[PDB]
Length: 187
Ligand SMILES: [Cl-]
Image (cartoon, rainbow, N blue to C red; front, side, top):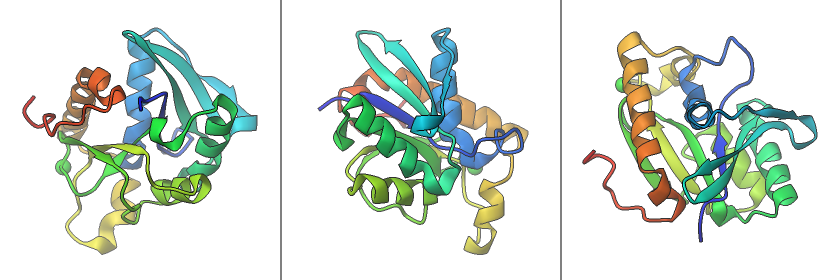
């Protein structure tokens, strides 16, 4: 099994593009930009798409234009259209459980209260896809979480997130080939 599709989770709109909830979108935006590739609007698939070369592999980059909580509508339509199985999908998302600068890999598991992930599990009928978890840190109490993810990181956090994005890009050939050693934090 190898990765054919990378979903970058986020909310569409200028007011959301800089927020912590959009770091998945930033990840795919950086891949596209590194490759001199633009996204195309695909309203019938509920997303923006770009196809890029990653050395000797290709992937479809997907930014759902649905808003976070209906991301699965886009992922499901795109997977159906390109004939891609859930195991061949990488979903990149903000992760509260690790700090800005940190990045982990995880196959499957529950949504952990993430609406983007819950929606994808619902539309696919399975949670068994690959996840790239980009740390945004945690505000310290659950009651502050919504506002936290809908806010911009500090200058120092943004720099740390950008670095963690670079780190995931450096591990991308391995990620695409399901070589998932816990070897990101040794970088
Ligand atoms: Cl943090």
